[PDB]
Image (cartoon, helix red, strand yellow):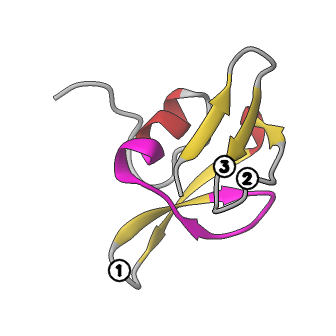
Amino acid sequence: MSIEIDSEQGVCSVEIEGSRHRAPVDSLRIGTDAEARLSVLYIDGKRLHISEEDAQRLVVAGAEDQRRHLMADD
């Protein structure tokens, strides 16, 4: 499940064996899953497992960053 972004319209949509989401990028949120010690994504208030890099782009897109401090380079 790779997270998607729509800068054209400014909407965000995640893919999950049948992409069926839709919401504003300003309505995104990053979380952490102690279950596997990985970062998760919140869309509409749901909890799923997204890719690390995809989790980074989510914030870059304008999504909320609660996992770590909005970074860029190291």
- Which quarter of the figure has residue 6? top right
| Residue type of the residue flagged with mark 3 | Val
**Residue at which label 2 appears:** 19
Q: Nearer the viewer, mark 1 or mark 2?
A: 2
Per the rendered image, the range of residues in magenta is: 42-55
**Element class at badge 1:** loop
Q: Is residue 9 left or right of residue 63?
A: right
Q: Is residue 42 above or below residue 54?
A: below
Marks 1 and 2: CB-CB under 8 Å? no
| Residue type of the residue flagged with mark 1 | Ala
Mark 1 and mark 2: span between their CA atoms?
A: 24 Å
- Between 27 and 66, the residue placed more toward the observer is 27
Question: Would you call the spot at circle 1 few (<14 residues within 10 Å), some (14-19), or many (20 or more)?
Answer: few
**Residue 50 appears at what percent x and percent y?**
49, 58
Q: Residue at x 46, y 67 (%)?
A: 32
Question: Would you call the spot at circle 3 few (<14 residues within 10 Å), some (14-19), or many (20 or more)?
Answer: many
**Residue at which label 3 appears:** 14
Marks 3 and 2: CB-CB under 8 Å? yes
First in residue order: circle 3 vs circle 2: 3
Residue situated furthest bottom in the rendering: 35
Q: Residue at x 57, y 46 (%)?
A: 3
Q: Which of marks 3 and 2 is in front?
A: 2
First in residue order: circle 1 vs circle 2: 2
The quarter of the picture where the C terminus appears is top left
Q: Nearer the viewer, mark 1 or mark 3?
A: 3
The label shown at residue 36 is 1
Q: In this view, does 42 lie to the left or right of 39?
A: right
Q: In this view, does 50 lie above or below 64?
A: below
Mark 1 and mark 3: span between their CA atoms?
A: 20 Å
Residue situated furthest left in the rendering: 74
**Element class at badge 3:** strand
